[PDB]
Length: 59
Length: 80
Image 1 (tube, one colour):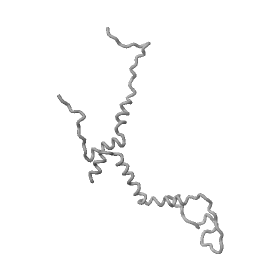
Image 2 (cartoon, chains in turn cyan, yellow; image 1 turned 180 degrees about the vertical axis):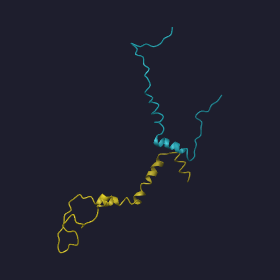
Image 3 (cartoon, one colour; image 1 turned 120 degrees about the vertical axis):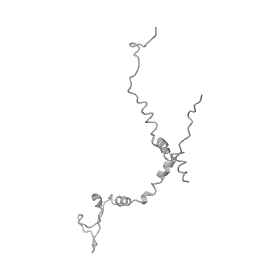
Image 4 (tube, chains in turn green, orange; image 1 turned 90 degrees about the vertical axis):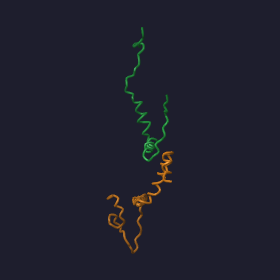
């Protein structure tokens, strides 16, 4: 069937521009999003120590 | 012209904020009385040596004693 993605007209009123004005000017974007999704560093590194450890196979 | 501030602040929100800092910066030094306190201090900073003068008859004011109430009062700042 259908789906129309990335197809949405803007708000264009008094208050909702302040959500798009604080975004560009003071960067509430790009740090709450992209500075937190990188860190996300505390997870365990899934590395195989190849001369000692070995991975799975199949019969 | 009332939406002209609302069809450019939702269109190019960079230089709009510049003109607001172009404003509110020229006007206010002519407004608050905290200025001319800037002038009274910046003149009352002694760089050079205050050389005394010669008496002849008068004496309108200011005898030789420095700790006498003979000159002005800039000592409001220490009380400020």
